[PDB]
Image (cartoon, rainbow, N blue to C red):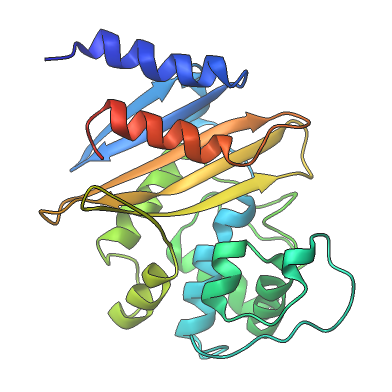
Amino acid sequence: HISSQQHEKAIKSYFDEAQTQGVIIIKEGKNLSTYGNALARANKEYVPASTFKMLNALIGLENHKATTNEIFKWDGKKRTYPMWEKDMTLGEAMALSADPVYQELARRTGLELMQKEVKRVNFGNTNIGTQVDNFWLVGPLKITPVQEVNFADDLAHNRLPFKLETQEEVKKMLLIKEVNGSKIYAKSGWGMGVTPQVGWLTGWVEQANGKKIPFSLNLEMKEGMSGSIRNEITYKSLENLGII
């Protein structure tokens, strides 16, 4: 019964109230819907930042560079955040967004194989440059919010060109919340290198009845915003639209 004018106004106001500029793309079946207070962001390119971890994991598992139970040991060096100073599986490193683990995985993959696989998957602009362990942070790899939600839709439905078991293993790593019989799978991103800074939350809702609704939030992060604004805006949006 709620007008779409009213949905548009409410979701816009969640971005307005967080004092950011951002878009959330929702995909239902084949239809893409764009909401937020900066709709033109939807087809602009930004660094994927930590969202690239989902593909990094698929590539590393498909090519036998790691298994899902393997423990990546902390090497004992000081790490940007204390929560990263511990031993982790890929799945724990996914949830904490632990760059050192995923950097180790990228080095095991190596520049050549990473380039061939990022091309084969057609992710974003497909260009990873010549440094295998930082191309997702400050260029040259870029991707639009439309491309991110289409990647999430592909993973949610097992349509990427990787084994089914590989896709299932990576999807178990991405479960971040249950809400009234609904499961949210998503990976967050915060590109602190680039100016302006970019924030992501990309994933899908799996509803009770089995339907999967992909989404990609993309916003500008400003000095001294909480990371959890990505979660709050996403949850409020999906709830406003009755998706969760």
